[PDB]
Image (cartoon, rainbow, N blue to C red):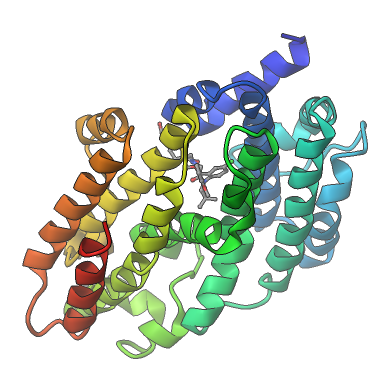
Length: 335
Ligand SMILES: COc1ccccc1[C@H]1OCCCN(C(=O)N2CCC(CC(=O)O)CC2)CC(=O)N(CC(C)(C)C)c2ccc(Cl)cc21
């Protein structure tokens, strides 16, 4: 390995932690192509996230990010974010980008271009409708699922349908993203960020921050349950997506985050703690899920068990209760 690729893998371990090993297990050319795509997305995200960067400066950065991949000397030195290293040493990452086969370069660059356009569109605004929530999620997460899918097909380890079915790929990203947004309500609040859609929360309270106040906890949990019900709608696509994967290392790569999100939604369902702190999967729980998620029958079993759990916990007066029951029944009767 070149020294620049070794630095890339060190950044991957710093950023993706226990998940780095799963990326490192990808077969053949998929390994480096995913590692670089991961780091490049980490850099894009770090620009997006950084509230110290003015909108005037951020819009060009987001729009032009795809171009920076091709600019050997391009770097960014003024990020105050946690993963600022991937921006300060972007030349190391971009060099390795430009060492990839062109069929992978072109995927990554197109995705970065489209994601940057969409991230720049949401700088001013908060998410209003459920449709806008899916648009925002497409830009920051659905397009990641689409890009990855295209690397798998372009590498020929998976059938072309995997790369072409953008809707199923998009759902893979939306499932994770909505789960993260649902779970991270409070830390986002404290960070001054709002991602829960205004059209759902405004039916319960006057301001999104009101869910942190004790007197509104019942209303908060109802909205939580409603948003969780929303996220569960992606699971049929997730099952379809995963069912098509023929390469073991790709399967594990794609399946592990999905079953972690399933378990996360089940922990968060009807859970007041979402509003008081960070609800997390026990490490031992996470490890077993990661070890088990290696074939369709096992992943389906895991989905069904957690959905049955949610199902038995649905409160009769929950405002979404029949919607929750219906999507769980749909999921259960597919495979
Ligand atoms: C669409 O997403 C897919 C699709 C297929 C496969 C993988 C992903 C996804 O990875 C999920 C697991 C790793 N993620 C992560 O950062 N960690 C942090 C450390 C944690 C473990 C730990 O702390 O030890 C695990 C979770 C990255 C991530 O969440 N996303 C998903 C979105 C874009 C919603 C944020 C991500 C980003 C880039 C790529 Cl290339 C993949 C992904």
